[PDB]
Length: 24
Length: 44
Image 1 (tube, rainbow over the protein chains, first blue to last red):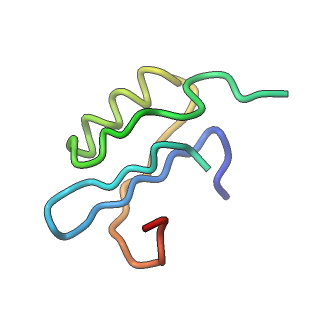
Image 2: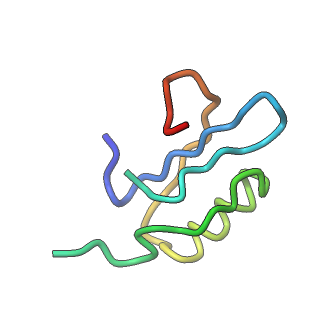
Image 3: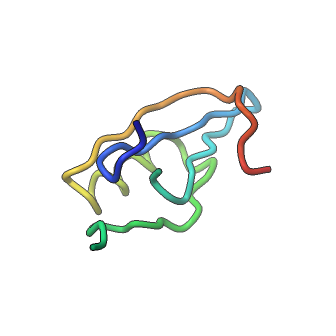
């Protein structure tokens, strides 16, 4: 359910937050 | 139609999750975000 009202942010254990430049 | 608010942000990757959440929540106060680790094949 990736709509324009939900932003997913990924985080690599490497100690960084890989947040997708786009929403869905 | 088009989705208002920054439909495509820059690249604050590694810029602290909370931080990015502030820019996203500040640009689109009508959208929420979810923090999650890695696992599925993402755009390499």
